[PDB]
Image: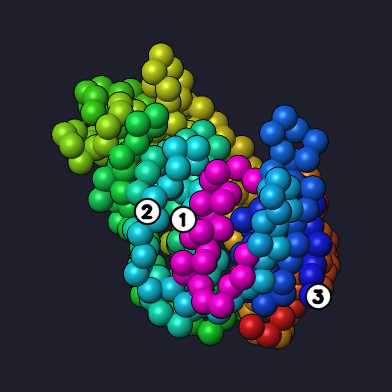
């Protein structure tokens, strides 16, 4: 019973994913044991269920009170499978960490996700489609898509999305990127469900108003969903994706609740995009966990990725901590030769 021991609900999915990638068994204890109703939440249990489905030989054990979990990783198998998500977490919650496994399995990942497709705290479908997967492609994952069959806005939901990754590779290519990602165009997806195309347009208006000074192209795809294919509830949101011709992407997202002013929601996403670009190196904060991990599991060899001082936040520290425990690998930061305070994250692969 050799375990790497973690504490709390923090990075629960990330830690479970790392356990699977490294083959190290882990033990997560004292989960929310200092809160009203400690233990795992229904969506984390659902998550563990998803894991068992896409792997083989995995043995999971949970205490009676659910405050601790013991995860012994199996082999990343994949295949076809449908997963029904509880109303507590949207599809992105389950789909995002599947990105970390799919390309490294024995069979294509063809996973159908049913449930809500949107929230305020999880990765939206567009963000995964146009914000995360492009980064996977830069690491050698050629074919990987997320098909939106049905959008399912909260609270009723009824959405349905299909994760299929045709490209199976041994490991991510070693990454060498020392330059700050230069944005040459801003794209995106403004969507709504079971409502008038008014909301979508007013969001684009609000977004374009703060982005007016842009000397680059700025066009946003409008994506109005009506009828039964749009889900059970009304809803709307905006995903802005800044990009260059090298395949890099910086993004931000937000959804609107009934009563929110679309122009303000639209403007808000554009402000966060500009913030995220301002603070970014090669990638934005919302992409580091994926990028860093793909580097760590690359062939035994040194990779390099420019980051910003602002990107070394609480979240980032914890990311490296957990990585230290599970893989052993520690990250070295090197001040860039230019006249800024940016660093070059130097990361040696493990030999996946």
The numbered mark, 1 or 3, whose residue comes first in the sequence reads: 3
Q: Going by the image, does 10 lie left or right of 271?
A: right
Decide: marks 1, 2 in contact (CB < 8 A)? yes
Callout 3 secondary element: loop
* Residue at (46, 20) in percent of width and height: 264
Which secondary structure class fits the magenta region best? helix
Q: Determine which of the numbered discs, if any, sits on residue 290 in the image.
A: none
The residue sitting at the left extreme is: 227
Q: Going by the image, does 147 lie left or right of 180?
A: left
Q: In which quarter of the image is residue 304?
A: bottom right
Q: Nearer the viewer, residue 333 or 197?
A: 197
Q: How many labels does the image show?
A: 3
Residue 143 higher or lower than 231, as above or below: below
Residue beneath disc 3: 2
Q: Determine which of the numbered discs, if any, sits on residue 95 in the image.
A: 1
Q: In which quarter of the image is residue 306?
A: bottom right
Q: Determine which of the numbered discs, if any, sits on residue 113 in the image.
A: 2
């Amino acid at each position: 019973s050799r375990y790497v021991t973690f504490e709390g609900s923090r990075n629960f999915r990330l830690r479970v994913v790392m356990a699977t990638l490294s083959g190290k068994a882990i033990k997560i204890e004292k989960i929310r044991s200092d809160d009203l109703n400690p233990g795992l939440k229904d969506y984390e249990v659902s998550f563990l269920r998803l894991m068992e489905a896409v792997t083989n030989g995995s043995s999971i054990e949970i205490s009676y009170t659910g405050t601790t979990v013991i995860f012994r990783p199996g082999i990343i198998t994949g295949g076809s499978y449908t997963h029904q998500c509880p109303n507590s977490k949207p599809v992105g919650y389950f789909a995002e960490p599947m990105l970390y496994l799919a390309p490294f399995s024995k069979k294509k990942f063809s996973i159908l996700f049913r449930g809500i497709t949107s929230s305020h705290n999880d990765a939206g479908i567009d963000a995964i489609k146009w914000g995360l997967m492009p980064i996977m492609e830069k690491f050698g994952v050629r074919e990987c898509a997320l098909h939106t069959l049905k959008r399912g806005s909260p609270p009723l939901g009824g959405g349905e999305v299909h994760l299929v990754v045709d490209s199976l590779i041994a490991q991510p290519i070693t990454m060498h990127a020392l330059d700050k990602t230069m944005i040459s165009s801003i794209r995106g997806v403004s969507y709504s469900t079971r409502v008038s195309p008014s909301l979508v347009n007013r969001m684009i208006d609000g977004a374009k108003k703060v982005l007016k000074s842009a000397s680059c192209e700025v066009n946003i795809t409008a994506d109005v969903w009506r009828g039964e294919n749009s889900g059970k509830s009304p809803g709307w949101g905006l995903t802005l994706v800044a990009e260059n011709k090298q395949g890099w992407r910086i993004f931000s997202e937000a959804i609107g609740d009934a009563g929110d002013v679309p122009e303000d929601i639209g403007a808000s996403v554009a402000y966060h995009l500009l913030e995220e670009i301002s603070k970014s190196g090669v990638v934005g904060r919302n992409q580091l966990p994926l990028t860093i991990l793909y580097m760590i599991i690359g062939k035994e060899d040194i990779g390099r990725l420019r980051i910003t001082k602002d990107q070394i936040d609480e979240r980032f520290v914890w990311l490296l901590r957990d990585i230290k425990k599970v893989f052993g690998t520690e990250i070295l930061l090197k001040p860039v030769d230019d006249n800024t305070t940016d660093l070059i994250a130097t990361i040696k692969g493990i030999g996946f």
